[PDB]
Image (tube, rainbow over all chains, first blue to last red; front, side, top):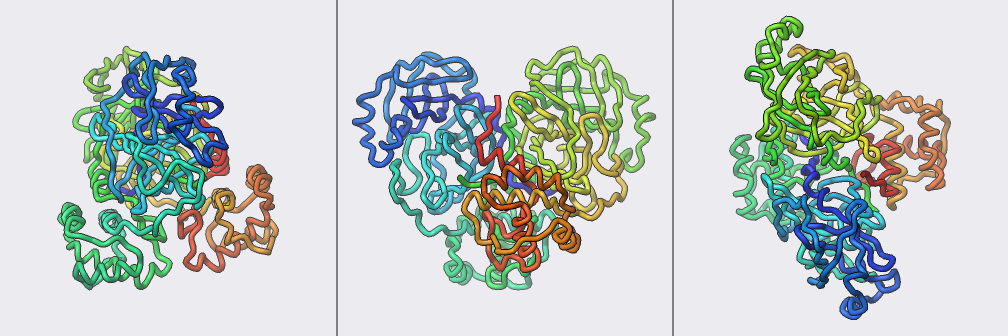
Length: 306
Length: 306
């Protein structure tokens, strides 16, 4: 038993991390087949970040201006192109560690594992959720740009995130592996605001089901509610509106624990209006919203990967 | 910036996980050089766990009674021996993925990464702390036994934990890689109690330094205190007694932030007596004690691994 914030095994993604140097900027790249993917602001100086014209800045760059390093071994760059906010560097060598992979654009509320790197070397791994305002609350120091977020199913790594920016609020923004930013963010050092951060209501509910599964039942109440009435309570506390889809997704968890989704919605309503009174749920004094319903089922079953 | 519960990259340990079957019991093993390490209760049936005589149970076992599987490939067992609570199975093939490795016995309060596995396949990775009562709060389902905990420095994996038991309280116990249990626990299905769980005081302090580093300063007070007087407060709240060694270990964090250790001890005293008043520190409404001072320095610097 027990329930934990858990990350996918990072072994497949580690064999894909390289070091990318352009001029005096060094960051991380992702080496799949004979292409290296990295944030396009590798071509920027510290001053260029204040207002970069990437097209013009890239005109002055050639293939031999990109230093791609895997271990002590340099890759030969034969071509380069800018797809949105990522640079695609064609190299002469397919990555012999290329796993089965996909590029996916996740939705708000979905989770993924981040393999934080510096100079192409993996430093650590942790779980992150795509906040409804398309930010993430991660851990990114200078040089972590290019670190990727991913999900694994069986043998397939689903790459979904690449780190590009830290916002003046301290939260993080990035793109998918096609270069399109999550949210209204741009790769410029200027004042950009995330929207109102709201709570992923369906994730809190799955976390409450995981709590009931593991013995934490003190919050189960004698009340029940409706979808509209629960939602009317959810707006006051900046919770994402719950829908029938969210209800459907929680069905398996409802079936195992025998607690109707609308019941758990009512137990959540009591927690929102009365607090936790100094108690904890799965060792937390807050309401966790970074576990999807699928994350709960995986941990409560034992899914493994090849 | 940002601060996160982070686990080491698991790629090196993944290439060491195998499946071990003895009779009808299947669990995980660790394949280093030409030896497989696994919990000795792989030789037990469900009834044997109630009172096992491992010596006698092992007499009836031969080398060909151990099914060791790496992928679709079986290992040939040439020898077997029982070191305390782990079984050492000599195989005819050195692991070609054997990394530089060490067997270490960590101390209470130290942290490590757990690569949870089922049937020799890695399922996930998360961080754990050796509680002062030598338990760990992990995530372990049926078949996770044999999953290992480790730390990485440069190229060296320091194996320190192997999972063997879930306690009737839902917490977890295991051995080092020489088979010696952490704590007074035995590999028997009987009532065993952990001691009073206490809080790792030096870990809370390093976490408070990490908070100040990342902008959370609302808890910094105008008071200071002594070691004895702070400790007198720590016993009431079941905190581990703080020593000069703990003070010394926090020196680097004291030096960077310019806050004396005894000051932070006084800010902790106010948090213990007045609570958090509904505020959060690094996104938590509790006082986290599973980050060592070294874990904080690593994240606030960017240490990487080869």
